Image 1 (cartoon, rainbow over the protein chains, first blue to last red):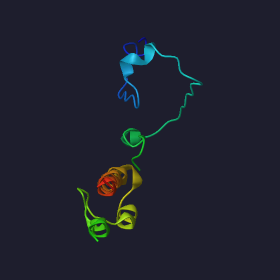
Image 2 (spheres, helix red, strand yellow; image 1 turned 180 degrees about the vertical axis):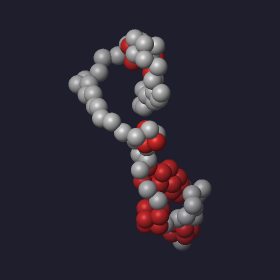
Image 3 (cartoon, one colour; image 1 turned 90 degrees about the vertical axis):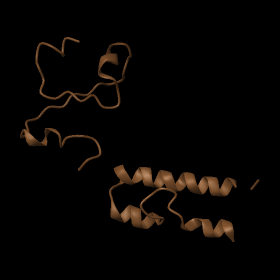
Image 4 (cartoon, each protein chain N blue to C red; image 1 turned 30 degrees about the vertical axis):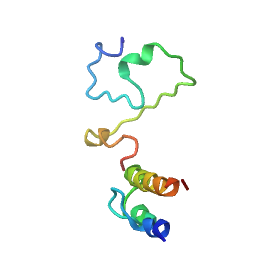
Length: 50
Length: 49
């Protein structure tokens, strides 16, 4: 919930899960990724689409 | 003969050839077409009774 208001993110697309429900279930081995990309291909980085 | 002839219907897809759909469009969309053909052919098989 703290990651929802402090930084107004341009895009927030929670795939395969409901964004609000992430608080009440225990996952396994969370992985984080980071890089820099142009503004147009942010929609391009999505599952399935080329 | 009717069961054999049933293998040439779309059942609601863009075509009725698996190779055509596979080679004409990407998987993440062709999955629904393959689902439609598979459901139709399962019904055709279950209609054994």
